[PDB]
Amino acid sequence: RKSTPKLDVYSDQIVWGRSPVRIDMAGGWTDTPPYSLYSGGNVVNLAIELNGQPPLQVYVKPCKDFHIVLRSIDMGAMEIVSTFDELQDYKKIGSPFSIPKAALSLAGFAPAFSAVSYASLEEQLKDFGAGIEVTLLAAIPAGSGLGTSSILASTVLGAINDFCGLAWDKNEICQRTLVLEQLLTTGGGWQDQYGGVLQGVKLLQTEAGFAQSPLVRWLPDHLFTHPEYKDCHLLYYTGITRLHLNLLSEMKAHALDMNEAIQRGSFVEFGRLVGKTWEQNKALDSGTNPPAVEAIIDLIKDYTLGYKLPGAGGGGYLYMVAKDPQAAVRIRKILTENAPNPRARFVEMTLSDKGFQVSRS
Ligand SMILES: C[C@@H]1O[C@H](OP(=O)(O)O)[C@@H](O)[C@H](O)[C@@H]1O
Image (cartoon, rainbow, N blue to C red; front, side):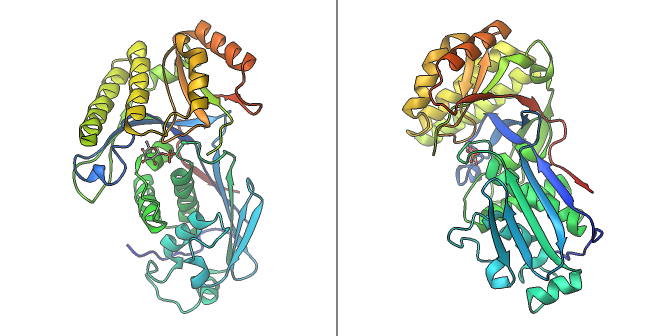
């Protein structure tokens, strides 16, 4: 659809949007094009805050000048966009601002997606009221596998939706995020944005077809929030930088098995199935388990029910399901006394009961 961005905020106000990251428990890759277009995808994932905060944040502000100012705190970068030719220049070399550019474009600041036709960006945001100033914060080393890219895209889209009064619900935010992924030619799946924007634990399912709008079924969060099991979920930043159809059918069926185990509240089965998801991911691709990750895994595999890397991974973050709190203390001991990198450390993850949230000052 075409959008009509209208300044829905006061001139002395800032829109703050923020989203947790996402850990996929099972079914990942079945959401990734093109296999999702044949059998459909089943993905059990979950929204998590890191160290008690939503990691993916966006500030949107009115700007005195009649242009667009993109800033990045985690990279300390800045860029000025004043024409449609610059805004739609998504892969400007050296610009880490492809995501907010595409998001502003989808919000009606590009000629194709704006319902009202304008001639220049200056006139467009002069009728809009003033310029726009977007400041991003993604305090996560890239290549984490935590859905950072797509969830940050959804966060920018929701911040702009609140900033312009577009009245998008979370589902349409995720759908426009899929459109944005198609704009930047990332070819990415749809698991990440639904895992991050929507609160709690979810099973996501699609049918065959090019239209990939996932059906969402929430799961109880007992195995993640109850004090019996809460301290058994460990997330470890490792300091690492970065015929098949039968296997993907097996991955769909395994996502359904994980859904069953979570419904029934079986913690041991849940951990074993996380381990099986790790085995499936290793079977699918060669570069899933770099040698440093396996070196870490060998130190603590005897105290876990299962483990995996979030998303594509390739290193960085490692999710582990300890057998019990005593085993969790043992794992923290081992990985603190045998750090595979000086930057390796544990990250406290909590289930997000909020998902994407947005407020004003
Ligand atoms: C298993 C794979 O994980 C990716 O997540 P990231 O590693 O990019 O955070 C998703 O973008 C893919 O769609 C796929 O589900």
